Image (cartoon, coloured by chain):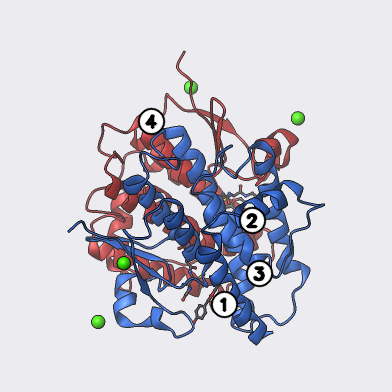
Chain colours: A blue, B red
């Protein structure tokens, strides 16, 4: 009779996969109900979903009357109510701020730059990738490489929920802007490490593979 | 001998002014030291600042060894350590998530759309504003109008720190995409309310006026 959060989702979306990765890492796959909202079917444009989220985007989390409409806020909230006593705890204010700071980096920099390119490719706004498209992504790689020089994972020396949105993005934009282990060695090593998490395949690779298939169709 | 946070800032920046508004609202203007980093002088490109923040952007907050490089994470952190027992408290997990959700809206939607237009204008990438420029801003207004129909302020019925980044942005992009009280009545009424906060003039209007002058020069 506990209230279960409901995650409105399409796992081709990197923001969605950041949450899926988080749900698995926190061990709460059984406490979060899923509700599929298929982007290529345009189910995010249905009147109910637009009423739920005027941004008409996934993911969305509904928990009782709480409606979160950004993967990054969903991730922090799931940590608060399910991860306070574990390895992903955000109880310490400086630790919470370190993690939040890198969530902001993903939301405002890395995913923004990935989505300009990916949205243009999907809607056929771009047919050929020019340097104007990939240079901002490589600048984001440069920043990530600095972060992963200063700590072992994106926000500190331990894995945190901030690694999950960034790796969801990294594994997506990587198909059009591949990581060079020589130019970004700390980032490549971190990427390889994250792919080895036991839940990486079901929480992130499935969705990447579906998007790769959609991109092969449009290119 | 308490450690004072240091805010690296230029108040022409809406993200900076979201923090300045927060600092005043929390009553901590005396607990946060300021360090000016002038964008038009290119002080954000100096080697020290780039080492501090590879994104070479303001604001930055340094507190002991903690370095936050996004206004939205700075705002949440200042609430945690200075506002836990007051009217802007984020101690409740659902309240924190509501506020964080609208910070994400500002970081990922409203400010992103404001900055594409403002950056293009400043660097002369755009000389005339076309519908491709203002339509995404008006879509963001449509979402904000929904939020302000469901609650009195952006995140709930009380003023929260989420109102401050959004009003910093709103007062900036408003100079190129004016709010229509007939098309967005709840947003206009909220905007007028925020302008009446006693700290609005020094924390936000000064910086807007400087940017208006910079825009008059470039247009
Ligand atoms: N900042 C948001 C971004 C969400 C987002 O952009 N989702 C995309 C898929 S990657 C979407 O649903 N797009 C549909 C649309 O924009 O109409 C988050 O992290 O949740
Ligand atoms: N998401 C960041 C954005 C910061 C940002 O874009 N700041 C701009 C001024 S509005 C800047 O310093 N730009 C300089 C540059 O990009 O080189 C935040 O909210 O702090
Ligand atoms: O934008 C999209 C859509 C999408 C949205 C609406 C629609 O009708 C069909 C596909 C689907 O997957 C994505 C994955 C990304 O990594 C990204 O940056 C953007 C998108
Ligand atoms: O981008 C800028 C710069 C800027 C950055 C670097 C520089 O060398 C000179 C001005 C200054 O003020 C801004 C205000 C905004 O509201 C915005 O969206 C973007 C900017
Ligand atoms: Ca179930
Ligand atoms: Ca309906
Ligand atoms: Ca002082
Ligand atoms: Ca130096």
Residue at the far front: name it. A198
Badge 2: chain ID:
B
Task: Classify mark 3: helix, strand or loop.
Answer: loop
Between disc 3 and disc 4, whose residue precedes? Answer: 4
Q: Position of residue B208 (x, y in %)?
A: 49, 49
Task: Classify mark 4: helix, strand or loop.
Answer: helix
Checking the image for residue A136, the label placed there is none
Cα separation between marks 3 and 1: 41 Å
Looking at the image, do the residues carrying marks 1 and 4 touch, with CB atoms under 8 Å apart? no
Q: Who is closer to the viewer here, A16 or A159?
A: A159
Between disc 2 and disc 3, whose residue precedes? Answer: 3
Checking the image for residue B127, the label placed there is 3
Q: How would you rate the neighbour count of disc 1 (Cα within 10 Å): few for under 14, some for 14-19, many for 20 or more?
A: some
Task: Classify mark 1: helix, strand or loop.
Answer: helix
Q: Is mark 3 within 8 Å of ligand 4?
A: no
Q: Who is closer to the viewer here, B189 or B217?
A: B189
Badge 1: chain ID:
A
The residue indicated by pointer 2 is: B217
Q: Position of residue B45 (x, y in %)?
A: 72, 42
In the displayed structure image, the side of residue A213 where residue B99 appears, left or right: left
Does mark 2 fall on the same chain as mark 1?
A: no
Foreground disc of the pair 2, 4: 4
Badge 3: chain ID:
B
Task: Classify mark 2: helix, strand or loop.
Answer: helix
* Residue A217 seen in this snapshot: yes
The residue indicated by pointer 1 is: A210
Badge 4: chain ID:
B
Checking the image for residue B81, the label placed there is 4
The quadrant holding residue A196 is: bottom right
């Amino acid at each position: 009779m506990m209230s279960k959060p409901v995650l409105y989702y399409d796992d081709i979306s990197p923001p969605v996969r950041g949450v899926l990765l988080t749900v698995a890492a926190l061990g709460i796959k059984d406490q979060v109900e899923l509700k599929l909202v298929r982007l290529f079917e345009r189910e995010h444009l249905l009147e109910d979903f637009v009423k739920l989220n005027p941004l008409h985007a996934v993911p969305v989390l509904k928990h009782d009357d709480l409606v979160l409409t950004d993967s990054h806020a969903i991730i922090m909230y799931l940590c608060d109510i399910f991860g306070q006593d574990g390895d992903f705890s955000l109880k310490d204010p400086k630790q919470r701020a370190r993690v939040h700071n890198r969530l902001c980096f993903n939301n405002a920099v890395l995913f923004q730059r990935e989505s300009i390119v990916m949205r243009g490719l999907i809607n056929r706004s771009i047919v050929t990738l020019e340097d104007h498209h990939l240079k901002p992504v490589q600048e984001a790689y440069d920043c990530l490489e600095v972060y992963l020089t200063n700590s072992k994972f994106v926000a500190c020396d331990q894995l945190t929920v901030a690694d999950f949105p960034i790796v969801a993005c990294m594994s997506t934009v990587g198909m059009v802007c591949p990581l060079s282990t020589s130019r970004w060695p700390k980032t490549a090593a971190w990427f390889e490490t994250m792919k080895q998490l036991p839940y990486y395949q079901q929480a992130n690779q499935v969705g990447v593979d579906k998007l790769k298939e959609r991109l092969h169709a449009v290119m």
